[PDB]
Amino acid sequence: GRPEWIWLALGTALMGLGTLYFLVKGMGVSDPDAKKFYAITTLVPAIAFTMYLSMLLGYGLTMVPFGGEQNPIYWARYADWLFTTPLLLLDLALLVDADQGTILALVGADGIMIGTGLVGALTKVYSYRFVWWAISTAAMLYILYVLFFGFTSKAESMRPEVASTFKVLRNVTVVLWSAYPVVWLIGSEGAGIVPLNIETLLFMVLDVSAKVGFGLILLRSRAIFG
Image (cartoon, rainbow, N blue to C red; front, side, top):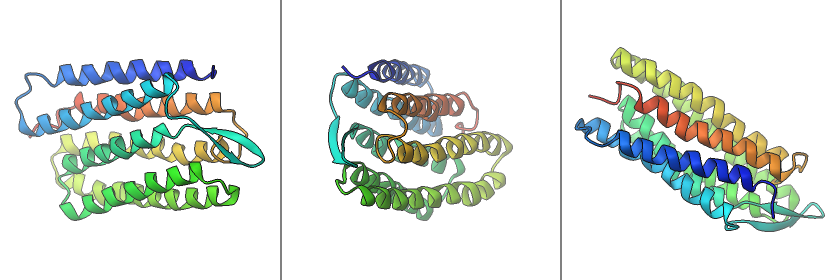
């Protein structure tokens, strides 16, 4: 019925395929630190797979009325990102051995980031749709600031393998996460200049890269081993 069913279907496969690949790659691995990373990394694409699968079958999609139009809103993405993104943050947290104080702030910021994002995607007053977007973006920027400025300094005190792998995951996270608030802004959630079918394609390339590709880079590395 909806033309974006194919992109919902391509993500499902890759996220499902990456789920087992990480799950398979995680078998027999004895290192305790690695077991932590494999479990976290493997659960993320599994969480996304489940929501990509439900959307493909016509679940988690509502029609929010704003801007004079009935705008189709995929609210299932927020149940996905609510758990996948904090695990991506915890992955970096364990990677750089950050103290609990930083983590609570990162996890708190992510909840507000994804929390407000869903309200804006469902608010019926148009203007406030963008108000909530700003708060979320403000939250995201705080996260990227901690990762870019805080975490990096810690990664250098570590051994070289940890620093080299974190920089790649930092640049991948910074690049991909920064793209999420813009697509939301111009897409069906806000402006309505990019049709919903295209919005879906851009979120998939990011999610896959921000999970499968992100996970792939992490679990192919020797830094997860203590």
